[PDB]
Image: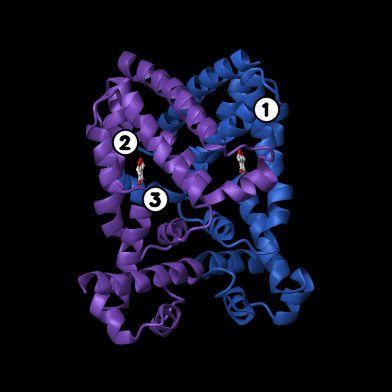
Chain colours: A blue, B purple
Amino acid sequence: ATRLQILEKAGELFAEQGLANTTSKQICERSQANSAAVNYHFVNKEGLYRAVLLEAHARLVQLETLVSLNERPGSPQDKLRALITVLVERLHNHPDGWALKVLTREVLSPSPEFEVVLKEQSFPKAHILRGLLGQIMNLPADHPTTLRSAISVFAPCLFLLIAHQPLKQHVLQGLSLEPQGLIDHMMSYALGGLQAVAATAHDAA
Amino acid sequence: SRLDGQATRLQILEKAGELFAEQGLANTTSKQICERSQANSAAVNYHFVNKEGLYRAVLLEAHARLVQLETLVSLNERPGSPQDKLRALITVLVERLHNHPDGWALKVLTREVLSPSPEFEVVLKEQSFPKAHILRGLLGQIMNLPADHPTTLRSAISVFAPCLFLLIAHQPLKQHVLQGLSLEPQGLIDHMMSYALGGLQAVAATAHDA
Ligand SMILES: C[C@@H](O)c1c(O)cc(O)c([C@@H](C)O)c1O
Ligand SMILES: C[C@@H](O)c1c(O)cc(O)c([C@@H](C)O)c1O
C-alpha cells in the first residue's frame, strides 16, 4: 500500500516534470512517505523511476492480458480485434493518465532504465502482435513485412492515446472517439493493409 | 545587413530549440538561452519580443522542419493522381526520418503535446490543421469520400501515425523491439503506400455501403 502509493504519486510527478526535474523530497511530500521507506522499497530514486516506467508500460496494456487473448480460441483476426479493443478502450476509460506521458518522456531522453522496459515489456508485447500479423499474412513473425506491419497497426492507437485532445478539437474537428467506430475502422483498415503487403511479400518469395 | 540580422535571429532560434528540446519550457531560463546562443538578453527580446515569443517561434520552426506547409501545397497542386501525391507526402516524412535521426524538432513538439503551453493552439491552427487538411483531401479523393467524412478523419490518423511513431521511436524499435527492422527509405515508403491503399480501399467499401 505504501509501495503502491509511492509508485502512483511518483508516476504523476515524473509525468508532469520528468525525471531530471523531480526531487526525492517532492516524491516524499506528494506520497507522504519517508525517504527510508522509499529507500527500503525501491533502493533509490533510479530504482523507483525504473518501477514507475515498468508500471506505466503495464497500465498501457498488461502482458498477461495479451497472453490470455493470444491463447484463447479464435482466428488471429478476432485476436487482433481484441488487442486493438484493449488500446481503444484505454482511450475511453483513462484519457487523463500519467502512464503514456512518462513513457513518451522516456522515449525522447532515454535513461539507463529504458533498455529494461524495452526488453521486459515492449519486446514481448510487440512479439504477440507480430505473431498475430504473421498468422494473418502467412509470414514469419520476424519477416521484414511483419516488423513494418506492427508499426502500421500499433502506431494509430498510440497517436490517439497521446494526441486525442488536440486532434479532436483543432486538427481533425469532427473526429468521434466512440470506441466501436474506431475499432471497426482500425480492424477493416489493418486487414486491408496486411492483405496488400502480404501479396507483395509472397511475390518477392 | 538584413541577412546579418536574420543570422542572429536564427542563431538564437537554433540554440533555444536545442535547449527547449533537452529541458522543456518550464526548466529553461533566458540566462541559459543567452549563454547557449552567446547573445545578450537585448538581442533575444529584439528578435522575439520575450521568452514566450521565442518559445512560439521555436514550435512553429519545429513543425516547419518536420514538413513545410509550402511543400505539401506544391505537391498537392502538381498534376498527378492522389496516390502519386500521397506517395510524395509520405516520401517527405520518411526522408526526414532518414536524414534527421537526432534533431530537436520532434522532441520540442512532443513535450508540447504532453504538457501544452498557451503557444500550442497556434501551432495546431496554423501548421497542424492545414497540413492534415491536405492529407485528408488526398485520402478523400482515394476513397471517393468528402475530406471531412468520419472515415477520412480516422484514415488521416491511420496514414500519418506510423510516420510519426518512426520519427520519434526509430532507435528503440530497431535496437530492442523490432530488431531486424530495415528503415531503408524506399522499402518503408513502398510498405506505407501498399498498406495505406489496401486499408483505404477497405474502409471506403464499408463507408459507401453504410
Ligand atoms: C502493446 C503492444 O501491442 C506494443 C507495445 O507495448 C510496444 C510496441 O513498440 C509495440 C509495436 C512496435 O508493435 C506493441 O505492439
Ligand atoms: C504533415 C501532415 O501530413 C500532418 C501534420 O503535420 C500533423 C497532423 O496531426 C496530421 C494528421 C492528423 O493527419 C498530419 O497529416
Residue B69 image offset from top left, x and y in percent = 28, 47
Residue A1 showing in the rendered view: no
Which quadrant holds residue B157?
Answer: top left
Quadrant (top left, top right, bottom left, bottom right) of the C terminus of chain B = top left
Q: Label 1 sits on what residue type? A: His
Residue A70 showing in the rendered view: yes
Q: Which of marks 2 and 3 is in front?
A: 3
Label 2 near ligand 2 (CB < 8 Å): yes
Residue B164 placement, left or right of A166: right
Residue A193's place in the image compared with B106, above or below, is above
- Report if the CB atoms under discs 3 and 1 are less than 8 Å apart: no
Residue A65 image offset from top left, x and y in percent = 67, 38
Q: Nearer the viewer, residue B12 or A42?
A: B12
For the point 48% across and 32% down, the residue is B189
> Label 2 vs label 3: CA separation?
15 Å
Residue B88 image offset from top left, x and y in percent = 37, 34
Residue indicated by mark 2: B135
Residue indicated by mark 3: B66
Label 1 near ligand 1 (CB < 8 Å): no
Q: Which of A167 and B175 is in front in this view?
A: B175
Q: Residue B23 carries which label?
A: none
Residue A165 placement, left or right of A112: left
Q: Label 3 sits on what residue type? A: Leu
Q: Do tags 1 and 2 sit on the same chain?
A: no
For the point 30% across and 25% down, the residue is B82
> Label 1 vs label 2: CA separation?
30 Å
Ligand 2's quadrant is: top left
Chain of the residue where label 3 is placed in the rendered structure: B
Mark 2 crowdedness (10 Å alpha carbons): few <14, some 14-19, many ≥20: many
Which quadrant holds residue A105?
Answer: bottom right
Lower sequence index among marks 2 and 3: 3
Residue indicated by mark 1: A143
